[PDB]
Image (spheres, coloured by chain):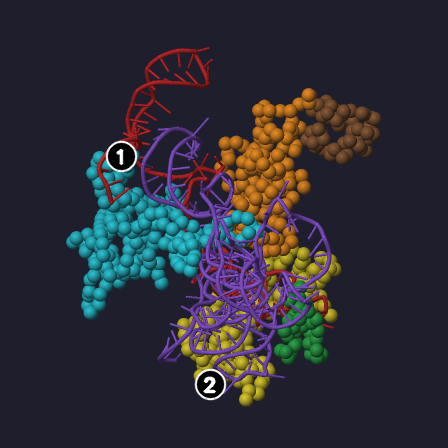
Chain colours: A green, B orange, C cyan, D brown, E yellow, F red, G purple
Amino acid sequence: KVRPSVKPICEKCKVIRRKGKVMVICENPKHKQKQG
Amino acid sequence: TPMANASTIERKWLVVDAAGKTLGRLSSEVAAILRGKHKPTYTPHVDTGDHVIIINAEKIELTGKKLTDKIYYRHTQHPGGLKSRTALEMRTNYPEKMLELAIKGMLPKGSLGRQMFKKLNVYRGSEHPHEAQKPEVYELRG
Amino acid sequence: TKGILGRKIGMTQVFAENGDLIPVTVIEAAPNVVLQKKTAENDGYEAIQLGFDDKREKLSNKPEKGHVAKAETAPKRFVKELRGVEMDAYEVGQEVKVEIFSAGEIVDVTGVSKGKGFQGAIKRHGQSRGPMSHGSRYHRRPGSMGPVDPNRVFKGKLLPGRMGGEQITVQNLEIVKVDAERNLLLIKGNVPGAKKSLITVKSAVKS
Amino acid sequence: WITRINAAARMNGLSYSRLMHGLKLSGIEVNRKMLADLAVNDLTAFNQLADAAKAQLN
Amino acid sequence: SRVGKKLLEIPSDVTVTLNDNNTVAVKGPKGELTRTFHPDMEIKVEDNVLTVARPSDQKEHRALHGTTRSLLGNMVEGVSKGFERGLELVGVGYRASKSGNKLVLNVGYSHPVEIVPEEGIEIEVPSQTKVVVKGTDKERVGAIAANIRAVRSPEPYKGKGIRYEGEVVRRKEGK
RNA sequence: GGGAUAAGUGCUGAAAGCAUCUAAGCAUGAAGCCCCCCUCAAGAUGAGAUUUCCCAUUCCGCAAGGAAGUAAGAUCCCUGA
RNA sequence: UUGGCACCUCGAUGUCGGCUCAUCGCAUCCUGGGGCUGUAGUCGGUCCCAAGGGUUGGGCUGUUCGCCCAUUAAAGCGGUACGCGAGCUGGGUUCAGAACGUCGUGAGACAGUUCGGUCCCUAUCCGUCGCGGGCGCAGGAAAUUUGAGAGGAGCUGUCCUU
């Protein structure tokens, strides 16, 4: 997904700032977010 | 009645090596020489150019992201027919248009920004056929 | 890429091998003479000038009389390059002719089109006529130039002009036969250029 | 002529922003700026004034 | 809780030079590896001990501190052990062999898939199921096997195509 | 078809011992971009190129220069497409 | 878009909509490529990049819009003086004629309706699209060129196999 309020949902989600974009990466692939 | 020269001016060929230099801080150091901001017989309308042959046109660095984020724009007179291009395409394919566009952006435009620009040459490093004029090496002021 | 050049004559129908019917051109293009070998050791690029359809000496000049001295033949009207053949198998003075081609060689063909003269906006660009009735006076004409705010005509707005006279490549043809007995090509389809104009018969860019 | 001072003051390694401080101190020189220029027509008369500048630049 | 202050041991026989600047050229039985390092990193080579002597303490340097050691820790122990990966074909009309040195995969596309390895890379064919790449550079070997997994990426319903050994595919119950 | 790219997808790996597509390093990837295909085009005053030609006159102006006749070629004029 | 304000124009800036000719912006209808799927394949929803190209023939009404007929890969929006009347058509609004309802005591009135109702211009300049004459290109000439740069093309549907 893509949204300006990128947050982890469950505690299995890491928040990794790639490429100037605060991306959240997790196990479950419905957590997959980005502001961009 | 101060002095103002006319057709008694002697022109002296130079060489600037752009190797570990930015774009960018030497254009404003080649423009002032092409326009003649160092000869004391400086009368602004009389083509005072001791002029520069640039060597190592293939070697120019420029800081920041600006190989890929600085982009040229050469729009035609046809509608929406601009052909833009990044600096990395211009550093590889032909930088002879990189520096000559830079100096042409420096100079006062008109009929001197042609005549100051007819003085400049750019050669890709380091070969240039100007043996028969012997340019002294202008190291830069920085 | 092989390529010869020459006049054409006209159109025919030649059926072959089936009940077919083939639209066939007739080309006079034999034989070419290699007059000058453009070399990348001197000029940067690789080409071969070919001359065709020799003329009598009243029509040829001393700058051009001496130009055929390297091939040592008569003066010759129609000269063009060809970038750029497999290097080389040619010598300056070797009479290139029809023998290369065959029934199956896919071939692009270039030539200077039939000039029709000064023609208007429908015929020159395929533009469409307005209404021919209903009181309308606007017919046969190109109509609206552009908007109002830029206050000018954008470059490229189609208009009347002189139609024709360009050089047109027409691709992917099929050379039908080879007639080195009569100096005659045979190409499927329509080939641009008016009657008896000059036509360069290349080999194509495939596939 | 302010350009025609820097085109001579930089031959001797100074800047107009510093040179016209030098003439204001070493000397109270009220030299005409066309004529501290002219001091170029007959160089190195200007440099010997630029020599007078550097002594109070230290 | 650092990496570049750990030590690299070379007993035998993976010999490492200080070929300036700074082209640290590993040798050994398997081959030779030449990683070029940026000039802030000042490698101090003790008695059989490769190290890292950092220039200073910035976030530029710290992020470059642990890497230049742990590139070599991949390199030096790669000219003794080598490196290899394990691919695990799961599927029905899916099989594997090599021919010449191309890797012929009859993945369920209507044409077979061939993967040409590079020099110093040995993609073994152990059996019909598994495929093993073997080489020296981890940024090459795993990257070649990443060029293999994208032939048939594992669908979540039936985990198909190329698949690393071992690996857990998230499973859906398609109905 | 070739070459670099978008969103992706990554292989390595740190800072933050693991992890982590990135921060150094290497990829792949679009009818997008740049060429390849076709057309114009050195008035591109930065006027490019190679081939082959005609020659290096006659007079004035001591000179700088200016005329008159002429080669290579072309033009007017004519039959036309 | 309906608006507010009255700041260019009331010694005139032609107003709706069609026909031509387009360009451009993408906030995308397709087509190319992907994350997620409450994605088993099939066909989708949704979010991403992407303007290169395509973006229909009617019936009705002046209609833009709208509905419906049948196709389609789809039948995108939107700006450009709600593009475009010194390029066209006037079908409506809003000239006089003429009626009908309504209102007024009456002349007449009405964004309530209806039938009829002179759409002028030899292109000066800049533009645009073709054609020429000079001159220059360190001597005059004839051929063939190179390509810095400029455009054009850029769409896809089926079917059969696998």
Residue drawn 32% across the image and 49% down it: C116
* Left or right for F28, reference E9: left
Q: Nearer the viewer, residue F4 or A5?
A: A5
F52 is higher (above) or lower (below) than G38? above
G143 vs G120, nearest the viewer:
G120
Q: Mark 1 points at which residue?
A: C61
Name the outermost residue toward the bottom: E175
Q: How crowded is mark 1: few (under 14 residues within 10 Å), some or many (20 or more)?
A: few
Q: Position of residue B4 (x, y in %)?
A: 64, 24
Q: Which amino acid does label 1 sit on?
A: Asn
Observer able to see residue D12: no
Which numbered circle lies on residue E92?
2
Task: Say which element carries label 2.
Answer: loop
Q: Distance between the residues labelled 2 and 1?
A: 80 Å
> Residue F74 vs residue E126: left or right?
left
Q: Position of residue C181 (x, y in %)?
A: 16, 54
Q: Which amino acid does label 2 sit on?
A: Val
